[PDB]
Image (cartoon, rainbow, N blue to C red; front, top):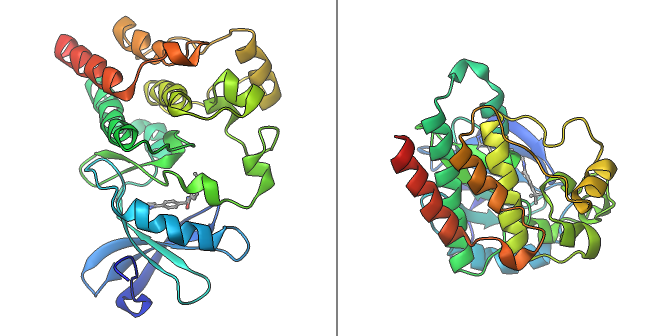
Length: 267
Ligand SMILES: CC(C)(C)c1ccc(C(=O)NCc2ccc(-c3ncnc4[nH]ccc34)cc2)cc1
């Protein structure tokens, strides 16, 4: 099958990290091309369902989405083969103060993500866990969105339950926390939090609160406030993502227009 990579074509070279599905390694495909290789730990994934969806994800192709190259499914553990991103996860990248980012670079990271999410929205495809930890950075400083949709195949109830200890409370709108109502507009809410992460250089949202306290405050209408590095116009964009009413939040196409307008006005 066109989605199937022969694992004998992989050369494993370095460890990259560990996530919800286990260890991820850096390697080469056919001795030449850089790849990341997720080694799916036994019992962590609804594997048959993922394999069917892998066909759909294969045809999601955008310059700002981390590309799915294929899967290795004829052995266990199965492998997911993706685009390699030399500079790793966006969250850690933001927290490296040596970069001494200009605010123009921060806005370009937001635009990179927003372009990927506009593409996903045009395909009616939800990320479901958009956040700085699920964005990666390549050798040119381009940010790309990673592991989109994969939350549907996580078997860990601590991650999937809204009261679960691993659930992304701090990236979730009130209707998700209250009713598990997921939609394009919960992706929009999370994108606003991601913009805040970027302009806060990777601070934890609601950093002095627990998850339980965050959920209560968000329901009462509390919001994140303006990062020091965000202009008023940039703050207006991220804040528009957090309307209590989901139908009042923008689309990613509107967010992209707004971000491009601010790039013109500030640079
Ligand atoms: C819950 C959810 C959203 C479904 C989910 C979230 C994360 C993971 C995951 O696998 N996280 C670990 C991880 C991911 C990517 C890379 C990586 N990929 C490419 N190039 C790279 N360069 C440096 C690192 C690196 C490394 C490690 C799985 C699932």
